[PDB]
Amino acid sequence: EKLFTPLKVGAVTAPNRVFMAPLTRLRSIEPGDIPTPLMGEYYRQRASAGLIISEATQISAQAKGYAGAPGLHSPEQIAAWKKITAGVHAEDGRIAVQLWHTGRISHSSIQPGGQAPVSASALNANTRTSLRDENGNAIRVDTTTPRALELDEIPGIVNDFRQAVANAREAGFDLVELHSAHGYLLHQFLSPSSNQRTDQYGGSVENRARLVLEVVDAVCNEWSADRIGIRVSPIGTFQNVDNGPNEEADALYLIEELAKRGIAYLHMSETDLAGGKPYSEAFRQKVRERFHGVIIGAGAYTAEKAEDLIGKGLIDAVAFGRDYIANPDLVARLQKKAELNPQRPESFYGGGAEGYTDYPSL
Ligand SMILES: Cc1cc2nc3c(=O)[nH]c(=O)nc-3n(C[C@H](O)[C@H](O)[C@H](O)COP(=O)(O)O)c2cc1C
Ligand SMILES: CC(=O)[C@H]1CC[C@H]2[C@@H]3CCC4=CC(=O)CC[C@]4(C)[C@H]3CC[C@]12C
């Protein structure tokens, strides 16, 4: 089956098209937002993936929106991630780091100085984030109303993405994935629903896409375009962030701009976990004719759907999320048509080994 055939993805070659989606698990050490040996073990268990895309990782301390999410900005974080990439490479895997700034999906209590988080504009996300209680357990909390970034703060954001990509190179990641989806900072600028700015970073689609394209250019210049992927969720609503009244045209504009940079891949998150409308094959064809790198699809895929769309030439790979949580050897299971392990969603976020490294292989 095409699912188990190789694929060139920028600077690396995936041996199969079964990718591990980025999956926030909120198990990092605080203080310091530091990856752990347990996280290293979890990723090593999944190293047969065509590509592992890490959990979303902070570009800076300001980027933090969830207690337990790791960073890639401090020396201690870099040191810990080096162990994780080494372990994946020891098993002949490939790993990309997903890099985010959460923007307004955050809480003042985990921001520098205990201050309001930042965004394109000053309106509340009307979403929940996850903090930790006094015993270290994950709890759901309402997001804090953000402050609009000043114009003079925007270059610093771009620089933080640049620096985090430099750090990713040092840490031995194979690729980086920019988190431009799911209502986080880059998507907050992209969407008219979250961006009411009247300067060069809001209004028109060109203005709304300006920040993400500055970030893409900065990180391509820092490392290489064949090391850079981007995740978008440009059709539908994700965590209360829609894509405005011209979502298809605006998506195609962004994709045409991304193509000019010659980046490694475009990762399309197709639906929110709470549901959304399917992509049409016509839209997939419009994306395909505008982007000349790898296209990854995600969002409640089955192997059957993946094989269908890869066979139709519309996408190149599929990222599985929850099936990868529950099946470290998902590749082997799909190749052999074996049953999958049951999921335990109660242990997706926070905690320890249970519901993390205790899902068995065949
Ligand atoms: C526990 C959990 C954590 C997730 N964390 C992230 C994340 O860090 N970054 C991201 O872009 N998407 C994240 N997602 C979305 C997944 O990458 C993926 O889009 C989602 O799993 C839908 O696909 P599925 O039906 O294969 O699980 C997460 C999803 C879940 C279930
Ligand atoms: C509603 C709620 O409990 C929050 C707390 C942690 C949140 C998740 C944290 C990780 C995450 C990252 C993404 O990019 C998509 C949304 C998700 C998957 C979030 C969905 C909403 C969650 C589950």
Image: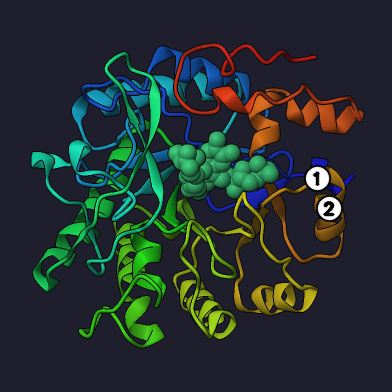
Query: What quarter of the picture does the C terminus occupy?
Result: top right
Circle 1 residue: 302
Query: What quarter of the picture does the N terminus occupy?
Result: top right
Circle 2 residue: 305
Front residue (pair 109, 119): 109
Whether residue 207 is situated above or below residue 162 in the rendered picture: below
At horizontal 54% and vertical 69% (from top left) the residue drawn is 234
At horizontal 28% and vertical 39% (from top left) the residue drawn is 167
Where residue 293 is drawn, which disc sits there? none
How crowded pointer 2 is (Cα within 10 Å; few <14, some 14-19, many 20+) is rated as few
Callout 2, which amino acid? Lys
Cα–Cα gap, marks 1 and 2: 5 Å
- Indicate the secondary structure of the residue bearing disc 2: helix
Callout 1, which amino acid? Thr
Whether residue 28 is situated above or below residue 220 in the rendered picture: above
Residue 240 appears left or right of 122 = right
Residue 177 appears left or right of 70 = right
Measuring from the top left, give residue 348's x and y in whole percent. Answer: 55, 28
Measuring from the top left, give residue 289's x and y in whole percent. Answer: 67, 78
Measuring from the top left, give residue 261's x and y in whole percent. Answer: 44, 70
- Res 90 seen here: no
Residue 142 appears left or right of 347 = left
The residue furthest bottom is 204
- Indicate the secondary structure of the residue bearing disc 1: loop
- Res 252 seen here: yes
